[PDB]
Length: 37
Ligand SMILES: [Zn+2]
Image (cartoon, rainbow, N blue to C red; front, side, top):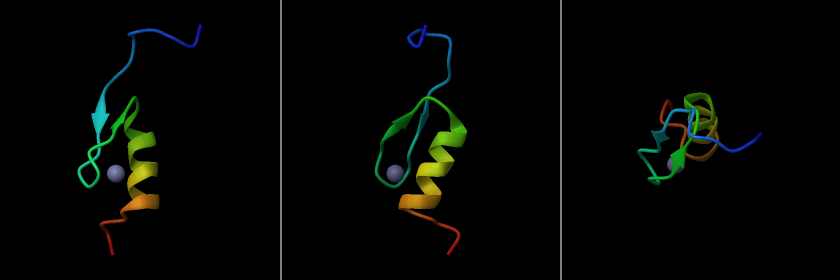
């Protein structure tokens, strides 16, 4: 099943969104904010 509590919580530091995986957060950061520039 696609639903459940068995996962992590991570957050954005530039638009304050929330994500269920750190790799999905990093994919959001490198697309929307890219702080390495
Ligand atoms: Zn963001």
